[PDB]
Length: 230
Length: 230
Ligand SMILES: Cc1cc2nc3c(=O)[nH]c(=O)nc-3n(C[C@H](O)[C@H](O)[C@H](O)COP(=O)(O)OP(=O)(O)OC[C@H]3O[C@@H](n4cnc5c(N)ncnc54)[C@H](O)[C@@H]3O)c2cc1C
Ligand SMILES: Cc1cc2nc3c(=O)[nH]c(=O)nc-3n(C[C@H](O)[C@H](O)[C@H](O)COP(=O)(O)OP(=O)(O)OC[C@H]3O[C@@H](n4cnc5c(N)ncnc54)[C@H](O)[C@@H]3O)c2cc1C
Ligand SMILES: COc1ccc(OC)c2c(C)cc(=O)[nH]c12
Ligand SMILES: COc1ccc(OC)c2c(C)cc(=O)[nH]c12
Ligand SMILES: [Zn+2]
Ligand SMILES: [Zn+2]
Image (tube, rainbow over all chains, first blue to last red; front, top):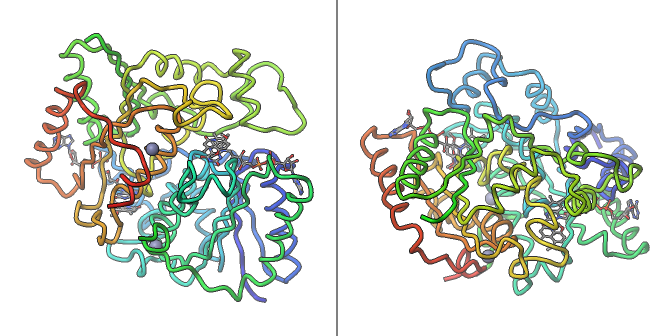
């Protein structure tokens, strides 16, 4: 229907399994009539470091630099660097944000971690108070579409890696729920380098097939119980 | 003495509270007679992105870029960029690696996330297969020293943030354990911005005093049960 989608994509290689999942997302959401934007972070050379270069004006305190204080104040004053504000505009307009990435060290690749660190600033994505259920991005949906080297069996409670949900907690709860997103159940595509040609093809189509009905899903309960059990 | 320590430090401001923790660590460990080296990532302008610039000479496939594959071969062929191999040399020589950083989004700042992604490469830190215990940095100790914005009550099992140990999982287990480290208990310094100028001292001293007997310490048991169970 009339919905805007931002895909934040973090993979160096267009011909990759990630590039395929990103392209089927664009193809399918386009086909439905959605408005679609992609931030391809590596192709943008997106800057991941949180530095004093992200504020253009007089610093609230130039003697002792505090990145969170200075960016909050820069956001209010409109003196944040324009690569940050460009991304904030995409996220403000979007109804659903999809993050497409390969799992690196049980988390996102650094370039994507830098997008989170720099774009989700105080005043824009949350305030104090104004976080978790009162976060500023309330009304928006987010979804992580994650690829892994490890197999599904490896990511079970009694597997070596532990359950897949355990690694989702900092991203789903600590970032996305904190900012007020409702979180849709993650898409995890396990061990596509191991899988056969039929199996990889089935994983791509399972994602295209899920996206056909994405606007009918309910969000997960983004609680400790969902992630950890017990 | 005779022990080597690497401190990988990620804060933009020398006068920061992280800055004071790093400086107390260098002072106390140097006083004990340890060999101490610090990687000040922001001062080094350390590159956080995983790209094809991490490999010198020609690529073992310049048509489909695969970071894991390309770096693995580059490592074995002594063809990694010198920023990465400088860090690996420090790590190989170290008996204890201390990471000193503010918590950003229940994780490390992206510049430190980038150190993990680019320095801890296959062949160096682990192999495929090659990990957890067949895991190449076995024998070394690692320690996370984290500062937070949110007070310790927020980080209780029924605080809004959940248990501290929930966010340590990807770093302690999925990164440090995976590579073979024994993980010392994390030094978590809750909420220094909310002062007082006084109790900001009790935290710096407990860290100083804890470093006095650091080599006597018992590693945590780095299991799903420690981070999650009862
Ligand atoms: C620094 C680093 C840290 C990592 N940490 C972890 C970790 O903590 N946990 C973990 O489990 N893994 C980890 N990995 C492994 C990583 O998560 C996997 O390598 C990545 O998820 C696989 O995705 P890809 O897109 O690169 O696969 P690719 O290598 O591109 O794809 C696999 C195959 O799919 C094929 N393909 C592409 N498009 C299609 C299509 N349309 N249809 C059928 N096939 C297609 C490709 O040609 C290729 O042969 C890490 C890797 C690195 C480099
Ligand atoms: C992008 C981003 C994401 C964040 N995500 C989270 C998160 O997920 N969870 C969370 O809990 N928090 C989070 N925070 C907040 C962050 O973790 C804290 O702001 C940070 O940990 C505070 O440490 P600092 O060194 O920067 O404190 P500082 O502000 O530098 O220091 C506190 C005070 O101590 C003073 N000081 C310096 N040296 C000494 C000394 N010797 N003795 C006494 N005082 C001294 C300083 O002058 C300062 O006034 C986030 C922050 C940002 C910017
Ligand atoms: C790197 O390639 C990988 C393939 C499979 C994995 O499976 C569990 C991992 C993990 C767990 C950590 C890691 O760094 N890399 C992995
Ligand atoms: C100074 O800012 C903060 C203080 C306390 C926080 O958590 C208890 C956070 C979190 C979770 C995210 C963030 O971005 N900033 C925080
Ligand atoms: Zn949640
Ligand atoms: Zn472990």
